């Protein structure tokens, strides 16, 4: 039932009241990976650090760190 | 470490160390660098506001899961 993209926005999202949609992003990557029920990981978008763009694909470093945590969290 | 600094806009998990001058980028990385309790105070970008208990709870929850080996 899970979807193909996820939005995380440090400044505009909430982990409390957000759902990882573009309209209502999560706030954190820790919150996001908690949601991920199966692989493949959805494509995660983050704040663009540029004034020009709202959104930007997660960095490769940030993704790898989230996934490390996710796998280890899948081992109870 | 008594106070950890985390900055999505300006920090780095790669070259940062959680100092106010070299903040971490995420709480994800920050928790990974805490090996003992009690936790340092965590400050996030607003400039700096202390971490919302709403996200601190998540960080301190996932940190306890880690410590089990
Ligand atoms: Cl995070
Ligand atoms: Zn896997
Ligand atoms: Zn404890």
Image: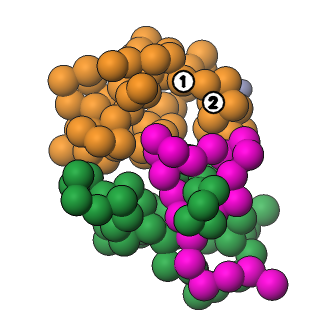
Chain colours: A green, B orange
Q: Residue furthest top?
A: B2
Question: Residue A26 location in percent, x, y?
Answer: 60, 53
Residue at 63 percent across and 44 percent down: it is A14
| Placement of the N terminus of chain B among the 4 image quadrants | top left
* Disc 1: host chain: B
Would you say residue A10 is visible in this rendering?
yes
Question: Residue A40 location in percent, x, y?
Answer: 59, 87
Q: Which mark is residue B56?
A: 2
Mark 2 residue crowding within 10 angstroms, few (<14) / some (14–19) / many (20+): some
Q: Which mark is residue A60?
A: none
Magenta stretch mostly in which secondary structure?
loop
Question: Residue A65 location in percent, x, y?
Answer: 44, 61
In this rendering, position of residue A9 left or right of residue B6? right
The image shows residue A73, relative to residue B42, as above or below, that is: below
What's the magenta region? A1-20
Q: Give the labeled residue for mark 1.
A: B51
Distance from the alpha carbon under mark 1 to that under mark 2: 6 Å
Residue at 78 percent across and 62 percent down: it is A76
């Amino acid at each position: 039932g899970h979807m193909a993209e996820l939005y995380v926005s440090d400044r505009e999202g909430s982990d409390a009241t957000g759902d990882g949609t573009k309209e209502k992003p999560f706030k954190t990557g820790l919150k996001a990976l908690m949601t991920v029920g199966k692989e493949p990981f959805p494509t995660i978008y983050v704040d663009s650090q540029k004034e020009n763009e709202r959104w930007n694909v997660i960095s490769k470093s940030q993704l790898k760190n989230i996934k490390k945590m996710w796998h280890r969290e899948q081992m109870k």
